[PDB]
Amino acid sequence: GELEALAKKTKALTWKFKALSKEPSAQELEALTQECEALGKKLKALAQG
Amino acid sequence: GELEALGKKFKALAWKVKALSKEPSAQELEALTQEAEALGKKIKALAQG
Image (cartoon, rainbow over all chains, first blue to last red; front, side, top):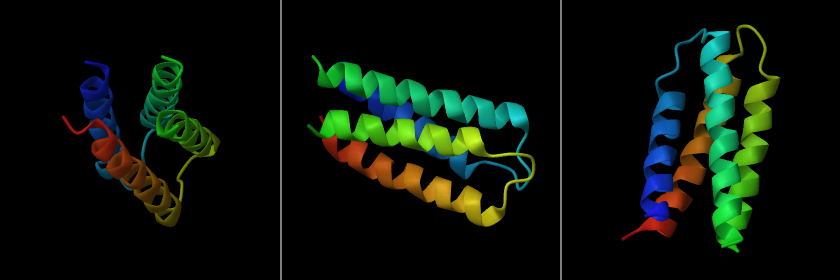
């Protein structure tokens, strides 16, 4: 369920940070931005469950 | 609770990534990576099972 889905997303997010190049692309950083925001929104929604 | 608070913290991190501009310093990328990893540790603990 939702816990495990958010734990996997969080792991994916942390690894994308860890795997960044020294000079990351604009697009990579947009993707990271979006993945942080998504996870924050999903946590808040589940909080209001 | 913790879900709400962790949610807000991911949104905060999203802003930090959003603010990055071309060639972010290594210190900044490492700072943001460590914040992700710290939030990751919290989520792992919260989602166990």
